[PDB]
RNA sequence: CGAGCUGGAGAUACGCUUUGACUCGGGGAUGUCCGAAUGGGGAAACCCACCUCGUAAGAGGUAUCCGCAAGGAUGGGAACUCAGGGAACUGAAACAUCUCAGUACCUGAAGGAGAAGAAAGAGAAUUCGAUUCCGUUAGUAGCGGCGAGCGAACCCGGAUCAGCCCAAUCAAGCCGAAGUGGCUGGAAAGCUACACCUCAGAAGGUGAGAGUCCUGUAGGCGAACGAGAGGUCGUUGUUCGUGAAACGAUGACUGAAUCCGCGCGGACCACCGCGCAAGGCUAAAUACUCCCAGUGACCGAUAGCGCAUAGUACCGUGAGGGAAAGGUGAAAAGAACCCCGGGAGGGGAGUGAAAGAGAACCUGAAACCGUGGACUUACAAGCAGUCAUGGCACCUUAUGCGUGUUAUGGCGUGCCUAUUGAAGCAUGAGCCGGCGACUUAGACCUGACGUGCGAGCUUAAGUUGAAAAACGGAGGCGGAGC
RNA sequence: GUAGGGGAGCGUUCAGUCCGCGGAGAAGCCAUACCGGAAGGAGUGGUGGAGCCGACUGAAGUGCGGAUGCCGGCAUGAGU
């Protein structure tokens, strides 16, 4: 049933890159990327917060309650932004480690 | 049928049956006078259609 | 009688067809063209043979309320179709002389309204495209009506990325259809012309 | 424009449908359903019973070249056997025949394959020469 | 290019089915029967148009000879009494008169006699 | 390649990862048993051996048919090819010939094709000059209980085009230009005011409708290194059915020459003309398609392959036959807690734009069942209506035009079919929804109409180009009939 | 006025083209007393939650009451 096959199964970011949220809800709200999933195009960011309730019927002392957890999103995020606004980065170079390339926009800070 | 191209319906300029006479030629004859000498032409205006539909093309 | 924009300036050449553009005529033409574009496609099990189904069913007399033979006839669900679509071609040959008259009259329809030509494509300056649109602007081609460029020459086409603006047509490759598809027309090259 | 483009008036009429009849039944009422071998030929209806044997030969059919085609119009292009093709007598595979039908005395030379009695006695009668293959 | 018959039969049908208003039984709820009911109905609607006249004319006639006998005549004598004299040519609506205004109809009766005997 | 991965798998636990995991490509190393199965047997996936190498485990060999050997073959393939063998229904308005048809089926063999092929030819010009395919010839010649009906070839155009040899760039992949505000909205990529790219405005995703947010697209780059004789007799083929019936082929009997030679040219003979067997091999044009890509005046699930996955459920001893079934929402935040109840199920709360989306969840027709209200009905015979009038109730196309319903009067013999004739005590039908019946092909024939040429009128195959089309005049119809 | 022949058009799907509509919401379904000579079409409301009218033209897998038709669902015989 497809799911992330529309895209090439490649995420344009990492699990520790500050990212903002454009469109949808939480406009302009930035957060640190935690869990990132290139298959289902899922993205967990400390930004979007959703108060869910874990179902624990007989785990012992269920004390069923409403825990604090995060929710995943799709391509509604602009990865890596250095001008305080959503950017794009395709330019490349190398620092001291020519085994890895980089990314930039109009500045060069990612 | 190819036995039609050699049947007495020639594709004339107009488009009718170039008939003859089937009274008597080969057999069963010997009476009358010039009944057999009737080897002339024949024509019909009610079968020209249901006859030319089989030879018209290969005129 | 259309005067060239870049290079020379004549237009008195060529003779336009009488009467002054007849709709009917173009009709027969465009239809023929679309007709040769219709690819033979037909996904139907017309035949009761192609379908996976046995030959014998119940009994003819005595089953009570049946009378059937195969379960692949059109009177049955999931079977064959009666007179379904079979793959064909539908591509005749419209008389050359009338085709020759098609575009001869097609162009005609643009000589009475939006007509434009140009010999000399130097203003282009490489691909760019951005400069290409600039050149249009200074030639009445605002970018509202659809345009068809019918010129040779690789770069000249090269700069032509846009939708409602212009269209590419390699080596004077005309249609009655393409010319009537777009509004304005740009013959440009005098290759086919005159 | 491309949507204003109409039709000939009579260039193509609508199909004929035997369904949705509201008083329509296809074909003859009986003995006409889903069979097509009766035809309209056979051999027991006039076809046979005709006294004809004849004999098929089909030898050589000559090309009828009317005499007015040479005479009347033209400035004599010299008929020969090649230039004549442009004079609307393109056939090939068969020879050429010359028959007199048009009458305007004129002096023209004729090089056909064969010709009639009346033809030859009509060309040289006004000037020319009918050349036949040796 | 296959073409389903969707949305076409239902509409066809509803069109018929909605005509059934006061129809008893399944005539008002099933198509094959409701539609069939109408055919017979058509035979009625039309013939009734032509027949209704035969009814009202007949109606008006009874009132006319009812009022006639009230005085001492009858329909055959009364209508004829208006024919003998081109004077009166009412005929139609005349029945309304013998019903609403007996006075006005009384004079017409008396006049029938004065142009008869 | 650059951060995730830990299969479809919804969940938990333990972990694998800058000493580049996984994934995507390309070669190896392991591959139990069954299966041509080949150690033997065997009712397949089981049982039993022997020999040899050996530390026991364990490993290896042991089938048959050709060969000194190397090696090769008995196997499995949807269709296509050749060969052996070879129906009937049907047609002939019956039916023995002929058709059907050398079709279906059976069997053998081979390939990514085969077949066929380098003249004892075709044919009538003292010519073309391997074979095959396409167009044409042409439906002509011809064949046929002379019936049905079957049906060439040469000439020419075109695809593709060679004759040598014996015996005496596509698969990974990377790089890859160009937007902000405001407003409606739950959510915009829309509306609005401006800006920018464009050898990239194909397309999909992203809360909705997308050039400039994402992946890609134009274009460029791109690897260790992976691909590219005669005769007789009995008969047959080719259009040829025994006809004047050649020639080729074959079973059985016979049996020639070879240079002033032999075969053939629709019995035969002379003349003339062409060619020279009894040896072989041989690219390409051609066919089909399991598989892959792309495309669509192809369906959108009662369609479409049978299957939105399944040769599964299910039926039969077996061969074999053979289904139906889709949709919560943008994303699970898919319902803590409370009330009734054993449960199911339901009601509040809450999440969400929506619960009027609640997990036997998109839309939710009809048949069928039920609740409520209005108007009516318990002395009249009713194809179930129609017309008229009255009573009552309602007034969003509509306080005056009617709607809904009813009382009564008049009138009134279901539909379809099949028929001289149907309400028919003749036929069909439980209802409803869906599905379902005059089409398609052959430059075919004929006619009406329309259109572009006009005493001329067009091309077929094909080639070169295709977001488009022209070229191609072998050929056909006009033209003289008898 | 039946078989039948002729004429003019409606509707449905797909396609090209044109003017467009749609989150304040399409198609579809549902109610209706309006309009056209018929096939039909329009306005408004309710439902629904994403796409789809009109005009011209082209192409068919194009219009159901029936065939002891086919598939599915649901009735009657009965609480028998
Ligand atoms: K509406
Ligand atoms: Mg029964
Ligand atoms: Mg019948
Ligand atoms: Mg007879
Ligand atoms: Mg087969
Ligand atoms: Mg009746
Ligand atoms: Mg009865
Ligand atoms: Mg009955
Ligand atoms: Mg009967
Ligand atoms: Mg009882
Ligand atoms: Na085989």
Image (cartoon, coloured by chain):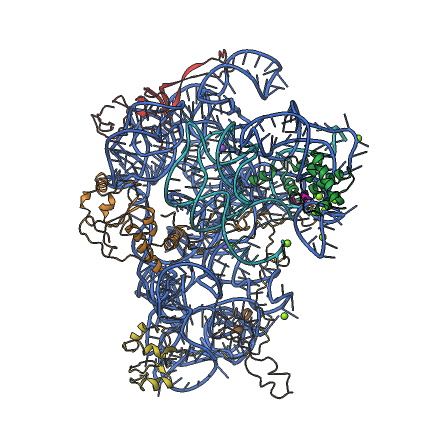
Chain colours: A red, B brown, C orange, D yellow, E green, F blue, G cyan
Q: Locate residue F130: give its quadrant.
A: bottom left
Camera sees residue D95? no
Q: Locate residue C102: give its quadrant.
A: bottom left
| Rendering coords of residue E35 (x, y %) | 63, 41
Instruction: Please name whichever residue, F437 or E91, is drawn nearer the observer in this view of the structure.
Output: E91
| Rendering coords of residue C104 (x, y %) | 30, 56
> Where on the image, by quarter, is ligand 7?
top right
Q: Locate residue C16: give its quadrant.
A: bottom left
Q: Residue at x 18, y 52 (%)?
A: C8
- In the picture, the quarter occupied by the C terminus of chain C is bottom left
- In the picture, the quarter occupied by the N terminus of chain C is bottom left
Q: Name, please, the residue furthest toward the bottom.
A: B33
Q: Is the stretch drawn in magenta largely helix, strand or loop?
A: helix
| Rendering coords of residue C70 (x, y %) | 60, 49
Name the side, left or right, on which F238 lies relative to F458. right
Residue C77 is covered by the magenta coloring: no
Name the side, left or right, on which F28 lies relative to F447. left
Question: Up-down: is B5 above or below C110?
Answer: below
Q: Residue at x 59, y 71 (%)?
A: D43
The total number of labels drawn is 0
Camera sees residue E50? yes
| Rendering coords of residue F144 (x, y %) | 55, 73
Residue E52 is covered by the magenta coloring: yes
Question: Up-down: is F92 above or below D60?
Answer: above
Instruction: Please name whichever residue, F173 or C34, is drawn nearer the observer in this view of the structure.
Output: C34
* Extent of the magenta region: E47-53
Instruction: Please name whichever residue, F223 or A90, is drawn nearer the observer in this view of the structure.
Output: A90
Instruction: Please name whichever residue, C184 or E55, is drawn nearer the observer in this view of the structure.
Output: E55
């Amino acid at each position: 049933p497809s799911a992330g096959s529309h895209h090439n199964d490649k995420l344009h970011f990492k699990k520790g890159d500050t990212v903002i949220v454009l469109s949808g809800k939480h406009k302009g709200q930035t957060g640190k990327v935690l869990l990132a999933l290139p298959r289902d195009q899922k993205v967990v960011v400390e930004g979007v917060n959703v108060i869910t309730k874990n179902v624990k019927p007989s785990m012992t002392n269920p004390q069923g309650g409403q825990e604090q957890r995060e929710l995943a999103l799709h391509a509604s995020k602009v990865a890596l932004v250095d001008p305080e606004t959503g950017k794009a980065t395709r330019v490349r170079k190398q620092i001291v480690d020519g085994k890895k390339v980089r990314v930039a926009v109009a500045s060069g800070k990612t | 049928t190819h036995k039609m191209a050699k049947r007495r319906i020639k594709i004339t300029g107009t488009g009718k049956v170039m008939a003859f006479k089937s009274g008597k030629r080969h057999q069963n004859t010997g009476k009358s006078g010039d009944e057999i000498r009737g080897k002339g032409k024949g024509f019909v205006l009610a079968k020209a259609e249901w006859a030319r539909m089989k030879l018209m093309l290969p005129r | 009688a259309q005067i060239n924009v870049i290079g020379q300036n004549g237009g008195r050449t060529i003779e336009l067809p009488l009467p002054e553009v007849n709709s009917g005529v173009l009709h027969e033409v465009v239809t023929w063209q679309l007709a040769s574009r219709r690819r033979g496609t037909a996904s139907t099990r017309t035949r009761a043979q192609v379908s996976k189904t046995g030959r014998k069913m119940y009994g003819q007399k005595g089953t009570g309320n049946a009378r059937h033979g195969d379960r692949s006839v059109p009177t049955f669900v999931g079977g064959g179709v009666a007179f379904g679509p079979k793959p064909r071609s539908y591509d005749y040959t419209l008389p050359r002389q009338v085709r020759q008259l098609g575009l001869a009259m097609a162009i005609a329809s643009r000589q009475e309204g939006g007509k434009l030509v140009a010999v000399d494509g130097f203003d282009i300056a490489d691909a760019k495209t951005k400069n290409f649109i600039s050149w249009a602007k200074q030639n009445g081609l605002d970018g509202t009506e659809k345009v068809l460029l019918v010129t040779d020459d690789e770069n000249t086409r090269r700069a032509a990325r846009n939708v409602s603006w212009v269209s590419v047509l390699p080596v004077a490759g005309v249609n009655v259809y393409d010319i009537l598809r777009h509004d304005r027309l740009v013959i440009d090259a005098a290759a086919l012309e005159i | 424009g491309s949507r204003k483009d109409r039709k000939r008036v009579g260039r193509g009429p609508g199909g004929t449908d035997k369904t949705a009849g509201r008083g329509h039944k296809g074909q003859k009422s009986r003995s006409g359903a889903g069979k097509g071998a009766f035809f309209e030929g056979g051999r027991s209806r006039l076809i046979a019973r005709l006294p004809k044997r004849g004999f098929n030969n089909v030898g050589t059919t000559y090309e009828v070249v009317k005499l007015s085609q040479l005479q009347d119009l033209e400035d004599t292009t010299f008929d020969r056997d090649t230039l004549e093709a442009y004079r609307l007598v393109r056939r090939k595979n068969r020879p050429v025949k010359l028959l007199a039908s048009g009458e305007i005395s004129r002096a023209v030379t004729v090089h056909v394959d064969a010709a009639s009695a009346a033809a030859i006695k009509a060309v040289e009668a006004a000037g020319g020469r009918v050349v036949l293959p040796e | 290019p296959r073409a389903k018959t969707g949305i076409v039969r239902r509409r066809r049908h509803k069109k018929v089915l909605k005509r059934a208003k006061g129809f008893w039984g399944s005539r008002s709820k099933q198509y094959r029967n409701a539609f069939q009911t109408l055919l017979n109905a058509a035979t009625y609607e039309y013939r009734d148009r032509r027949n209704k006249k035969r009814d009202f004319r007949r109606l008006w006639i009874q009132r006319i000879n009812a009022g006639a006998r009230l005085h001492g005549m009858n329909y055959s004598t009364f209508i004829n009494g208006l024919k003998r004299a081109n004077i009166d040519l009412n005929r139609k609506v005349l029945a309304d008169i013998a019903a609403r205004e007996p006075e006005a109809f009384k004079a017409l009766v008396d006049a029938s006699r004065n142009a008869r005997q």
